[PDB]
Image: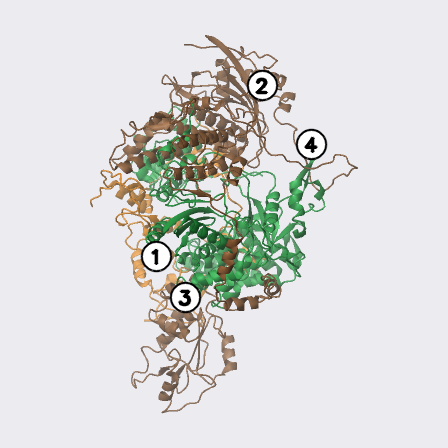
Chain colours: A green, B orange, C brown
Amino acid sequence: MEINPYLLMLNNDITSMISLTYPYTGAPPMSHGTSTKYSMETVSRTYSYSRTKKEVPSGIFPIERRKFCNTIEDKENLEKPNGNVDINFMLSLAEMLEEKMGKGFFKFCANEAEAEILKMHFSKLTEGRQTYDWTSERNMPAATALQLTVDAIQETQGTFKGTTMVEYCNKILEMMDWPEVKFKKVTLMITKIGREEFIKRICTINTMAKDGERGKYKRRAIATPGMGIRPFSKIVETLAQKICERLAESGLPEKKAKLKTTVSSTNSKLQEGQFMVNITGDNSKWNECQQPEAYLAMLAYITKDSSNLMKDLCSVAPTLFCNKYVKMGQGFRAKNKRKTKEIVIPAKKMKERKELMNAEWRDLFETIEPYMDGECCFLGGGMLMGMFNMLSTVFGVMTLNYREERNCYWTGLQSSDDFVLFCISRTWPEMEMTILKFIAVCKLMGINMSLEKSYGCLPELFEFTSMFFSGDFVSNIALELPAFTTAGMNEGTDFTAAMSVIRTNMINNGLSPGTALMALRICLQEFRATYRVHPYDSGVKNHRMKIIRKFIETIENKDGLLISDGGKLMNNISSLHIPEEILKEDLMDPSYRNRVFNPRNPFTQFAVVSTHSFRTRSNRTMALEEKRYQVVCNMYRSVFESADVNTPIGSMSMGEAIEAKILDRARTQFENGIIGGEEYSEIKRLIEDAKRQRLS
Amino acid sequence: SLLLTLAKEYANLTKDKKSCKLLSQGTVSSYTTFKKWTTSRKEKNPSLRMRWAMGSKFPIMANREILEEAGIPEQWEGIDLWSKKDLGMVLASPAAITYWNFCGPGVDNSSVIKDVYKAKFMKKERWRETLWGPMNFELVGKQRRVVETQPVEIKLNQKEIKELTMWVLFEDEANLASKFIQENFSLVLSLRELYKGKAVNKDVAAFMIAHQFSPEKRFLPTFGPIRPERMELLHCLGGDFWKIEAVTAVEGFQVCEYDPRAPLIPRRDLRLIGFGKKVRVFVGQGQEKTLVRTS
Amino acid sequence: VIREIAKRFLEQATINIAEEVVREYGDHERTMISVGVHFQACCLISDEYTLEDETTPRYVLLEGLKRQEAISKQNNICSTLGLEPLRNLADIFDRKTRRFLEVGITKRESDEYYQEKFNKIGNDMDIHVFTYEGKYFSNNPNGLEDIQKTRIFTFLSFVSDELRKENMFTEMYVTEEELEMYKSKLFIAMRDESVPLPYINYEHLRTRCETFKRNQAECEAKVADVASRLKIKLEHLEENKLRPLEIPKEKEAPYTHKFLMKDAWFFAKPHDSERAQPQQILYDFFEAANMGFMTTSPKPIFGKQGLMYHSLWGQTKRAIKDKRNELEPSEQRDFLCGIGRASKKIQEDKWQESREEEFKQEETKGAAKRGFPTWFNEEWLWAMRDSKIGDWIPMAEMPPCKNEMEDYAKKMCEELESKIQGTNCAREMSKLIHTIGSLHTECRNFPGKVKIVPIYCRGTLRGESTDCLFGIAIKGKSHLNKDDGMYTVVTFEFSTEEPNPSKHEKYTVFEAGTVPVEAKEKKLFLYCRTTGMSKLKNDWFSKCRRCLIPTMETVEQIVLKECALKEENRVSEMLENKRAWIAHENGENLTRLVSTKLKDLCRMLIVTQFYYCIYNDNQLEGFCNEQKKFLMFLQADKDSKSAFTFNQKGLYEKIEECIVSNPLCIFLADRLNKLFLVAKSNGAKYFE
């Protein structure tokens, strides 16, 4: 007897029979070796999508430049993706955009975005993902990269007194005007660097392999930039963020009711012969056909009447993208016929060691060589991942508010690379006319729709952001399984945090009640499997159940134990927002309650109730800067006991209010307190000697 | 310490030149990056590393003097609970944690814990005294709203709460005393008589005041009535294809200028050495002036 | 927000007046707030004590006002006394001092601004400079004892604290004494260089962008794009070319699972509470399972390497006989688990060049392709058949229920839990959790040491808690730095069935002996297979218990969809009186399906979720995405909505590209083609 699991789909919808077809339970695929060939295919494929040969030599950079706008060579295979943008066409789409809603649109949104840049501190640059520090030329979090950048500022010339976005970016432009920058290397020797290498290093973007990406056979390379390009991108994301929030045909922040209103609204505006066909579409190669020259052009049109600071200020990050460098990974490997000795050739010696490569590597390499640096590569038309995402959606709305003038048209909804298009027309060859005009406007603007991964029907049966929508019913987002148990901090913060995660997936997603009860008991099971705690009636005999089983006659009311202390579950689905201790302190024994909840414990001393909070041992496998800086942290935190709650205002001096603070509370505790001359005169001598030692 | 040795370690640990290049001549803003600076990059699998920790023999870094003051080195059958390695911090087992939980001393802390977490105990009291009934098994669906989900009786706007705690605990470096603060200054006048003498940590006091008064606004899918008592139970009351509910029911002082040689008298002696004098006031983060009382 | 914070500290109505001044000033943004502060400065100067006897006010306010009536009121106040201007329009006129009244407020120390004003006017006016810091540094005539100075330093410390709230320091700048970017030297040639090709500099581009109007020649380029297109949509009612997939007609894919599911044999004993560590269970089953009768011939039935497995098995047999789990170094473990078998990683410091000796290069191949497996259906049907041993999976307890829907969710957990514990899949998941857990903790606690970790289970037999023993695992001195590392595991397995050179391709089957079986004494085979796990593979296979969530998610969506469409509490009969069409027979397929109950359906759902937890690869992911596309096509067939596709050529190139050697992928492709046969038995979009 044969068997087929899919046969349930012969009599049911797809709103429930689609979580069957997600393999989200096993291990994600991971990368191996280097991420060099992926970047070579990305850059060589991007220049291979340029449809041009017209080059402009550079007098600033020692490498050539190939233009991308208004330089087309119309090949016959136009279904192949192109990388060319017509600028008067998209400016006509901008005037066609603003003529639909309002007149002072970019002026009002530019007054809001201009209104919310000057009141921003530059510490927002530290609240990000992993970045690329250029001091040791590695990947570090943003606090370390901003730390070494500000340290290079106060190390090379002068100090930093900015404390803003604008004076810090003007300080970066001052660093671009500096002829020589001194920073630290290795044990901290201060080396110097010239003017051109600072230019070649600040415009360097690192490429690695995207790890843990579900849904692709071939891996795709992700790129992380440095620090001196991030804040201008933050400015652009504030501007386009307010643009997308002001719009009504974007879904970057509810994503559900907008489809209800456009389906119900545009079905209310049909003729007696007109009808509607929707197409699910997915733009392929989305990150290789968005040249930042069009961002320079449109951001020169959005800011046409804004200011003088903002008009020059939104014209730097696309310029930094038009001359960006691409890292080449870490090289490759070479071995003999016996396959024993294998030398490793980096990206530096790849030019000299060209003759030890495969055919595919040499096909990607001979087509990339005249745009290579000695250690990096040059790109001027790409837009990789980790870049402008709230701004290409505006291009989606500009493609989705076109007027051609019958009375046949379209509307729809855009995402990062998914789009749902709603066409209204009369006949099927006229549907070919309207669809091929949509491919005309997207292809002329530079949005390359995949022809294999797009389809459509007459009513609502479409895909949007992995949410398959029926004619009446709605499927849910496929939830991540390993997001449930990744707390790993404490015997109290692993279960209640799991109740927070199951609570948030219950509110946000559908997440039927018995499924949440089952996942609750599974997470309870892995909690009792992690910390080796069993219920008292269970006959598990290890090094910790011996004490509990020995001392169980001391407890009168047995359900007053904790799950981390040898008790069964009392939390429920109606008790996910309440921790176990608050539910269980009303049934505890008073010797147990006074015994466990002692703050005089040798484990806690040296957002839940902390009674089991211990610290495990660190590993055994930049170490003076953490010592000095945490001396500043524990010192300034020790002076001001309430300072991690409020923002540390006051930038005139730190230690002057410290010295007047120790004089203040020493005199305050002194004058109708201590009263003894050697302590007040002694601490007075320490403050005076520290002030004369410091100020000189 | 008791504020006698902090000037000694302040004097001894400011002998560095780069400390003077940093303090009072560098970046005060970088303290906001000094708080979050450590080399803990991502910890991509923390529960895996905790599972590696619980599989070792003595993973726990615990204090020495308390457990050697009270505890016992080995249990009744070979259970090792100690180490002799190092600073003064001794590795230990969670069997010492549960041995503290069964054979440790007791400290009466009933009113403390039953006064810190009063919001969540009130959640338990309002959950204990509710009542349900039958279900519906009907279709339901409604858009997402912005609802504040806690039955508070003050309803600040997430800005007067930090400013309130600073203007209750330590009013010196606190914030402005603003025009949206005169009624809140009556609230401090009602709350200076509560948070004066406590054995509570200041971070815990800022936690309990920061949570007992704040209506937590969220962007959640709601349905039916939007009364905030039944909004924190939104995960229990409904799903997508089912619905269940059967609930039937004093320093009013002033400063003038900065010039005169004022007597060195702080805010503790601000009332008795108050009126008719030009008495200086040290305001917090560095702004210290001279005071004249204005009627 | 400028306006929201601007309504906090600054007054209500004054926003419109100061904003009205900025409307009469020009394109400037920050100065609004400053002018408002200045206006409230005037509101603290000229409000309550404006020379009440002779009620015509001492402070003639002609600065913050409409720019029509300052000259007229100037000629209405000064027409009696008569004054002289001092090269500037005065802020506030005065008749008690018979002078002007200058108002200016600064952030810095007030020396430099007062010297700049001293260069502008000198001290011939009446200068009033007020500082946020608290410095009354102004002209010599002053206010006598009034509360205007007290309230104005209260107000400047007030608004100064508002500046210290939201970081507003480069925002109170007077235009004469922010809106200019730092014009460098190298960026200005950079911005002009990356302009588009018909443009010279950024200036001409910006002036054209500010003076652009759209034209109707856009449609000439649009239809000019329509002409050179050569693209048509492809319908489905007339050209339904949804052809069956190209399964490779090649060598059959072998049994590729890390362990054995159906071909296993085990030994039982009653489990002890004290004897609980894996070495203790290994020794207790060394006396329980008799290894003295474990005699292996030196000639294998088939395979490649027989002698190293023979001496390795005898060596670990005398190793567990001495009750210590650590193999002494000999050539067998030096050959099997990779010891000294690695590439000499040579950096680029010296190369020791030679005339064509050790000519090194690089070479990649890809993946080998196989054919359709036929042994997989028997393990599917074996996998959903009940075995008499009871519970396998250690699940936790049930919380106490209220009068809520906890009776419903408790009912679903108790029925589904009561059905999933008896299946052989629960035995396999217990095998993976216990064995992969113990090998994981041995991969932590002892790197560099070859250990002997048994392969076992634990289940309830006649109510009494017993344990099993399936195989022997040997660790390969794992030094797991990153998530990879690929440490070698050697597996010696126990089987009670005859081998297969087609299915068991990766094995080196020996013969062990005889097994007594009650119902005579059949045979006993020992299997050998070397393999390699990973750390991330230990993390994801060691936590394979969380497969109940999509299964119970699916079943509970079926039940809640059904009673959501029936609007009545019909659950306990819906869990019994509902059919599910599965398992078409082998000989015929045309409308010949088997309606089963719902509990066997959730059995098969935990089967396919478990097989998804085993075989998770790239080909599975791309194959699952493309089969989501085919399910969308089939759902489009279920209502005859006339779907359409632009290119049906490269779609099968993408599907057949990611079908190489995964047997689950090939199997679900084959069953997908049979699904197209059953959908072709009723609907009209498909082939034979």
**Farthest residue toward the right?**
C355
Of labels 1 and 3, the one closer to you: 3
Alpha-carbon span between mark 3 and mark 2: 80 Å
Of labels 4 and 3, the one closer to you: 3
Above or below residue C328? Residue A107 is below
Q: For residue B157, which numbered disc appears in the image? A: 1
Q: Quadrant of the C terminus of chain A?
A: bottom right
Task: Name the kind of residue labelled 2 in the image.
Answer: Thr
Does A68 sit left or right of A659 as displayed?
A: right
- Residue beneath disc 3: A103
Could you tell me residue B24's position as x and y percent? 53, 61
Task: Name the kind of residue labelled 4 in the image.
Answer: Thr
Alpha-carbon span between mark 2 and mark 1: 73 Å
Q: Secondary structure at mark 4?
A: loop
Q: Residues within 10 Å of mark 4 (few under 14, many from 20)?
A: few
Could you tell me residue B213's position as x and y percent? 32, 52
**Farthest residue toward the left?**
B248
Q: Residues within 10 Å of mark 1 (few under 14, many from 20)?
A: few
- Image quarter of residue C54: bottom left
Q: Quick one: A383 or C134, which is closer to the camera? A: A383
In which chain is the residue bearing label 1?
Answer: B
Task: Name the kind of residue labelled 3 in the image.
Answer: Lys
Q: Residues within 10 Å of mark 2 (few under 14, many from 20)?
A: many
Q: Secondary structure at mark 1?
A: loop
Q: For residue C670, which numbered disc appears in the image? A: none
Q: Quadrant of the N terminus of chain A?
A: top left
